[PDB]
Image (cartoon, rainbow, N blue to C red; front, side, top):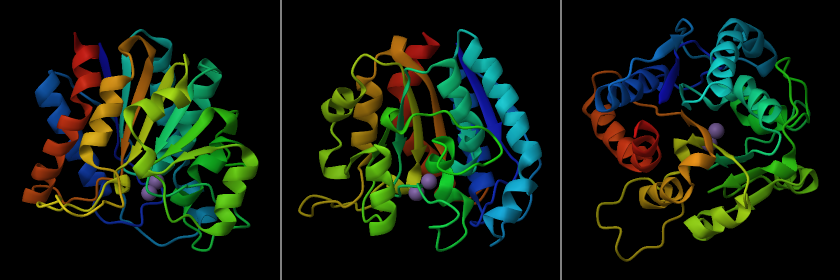
Length: 271
Ligand SMILES: [Mn+2]
Ligand SMILES: [Mn+2]
């Protein structure tokens, strides 16, 4: 009852290993849950190109992800996308909002990803994902997601300009220290739920985390969200931006933490 879709095409990647990180994540879920992913797109080297150039490079991959996610959302399974970058979601979130206008999008991310072409400092498409899906600029892949239905979770240290775009559009923000399971549940109400996770929301690992207050979200906070969202209400889950090299020990240790965080939702969906 899980539909696993994996992006392997470049969508504006500026980091070197997020396509490999996607591949390693999908593999772990394949082995644990007895699935075989639908892989989409052809890998390409990362680059520091303007969104105006990277977005058209990505059209083929984005279109094929849209078709595969659309297929999945209209079915009866849990839709799980393992994405190299958040920018893949320029294709999926408009589908989510059209099939499920009442869906709340939990955009879990250390950043706001709410830049527009006029406000971006870096030109990075990954920083314009939620604003594009909400229609503040036109990505060429649709919009229709109400900002009132989007909730940023774990975001912090947002640029004052971008924080005002977020505020004016009506996107709620729940910082890591407020991001308990109940706070998230209270933001969702009865609605069906789409979960999008950029792993940079996570606190950089501390083994003795005992006496410091973390700035990012902890894995246990991610797991509690997945434990708290009722299975009948979960539309799907996007896992994005694991930057870890193929065959590396680090990728192996990374996907073990991911599988522990996602296990409550995926185990419920599997049976
Ligand atoms: Mn992101
Ligand atoms: Mn981020």
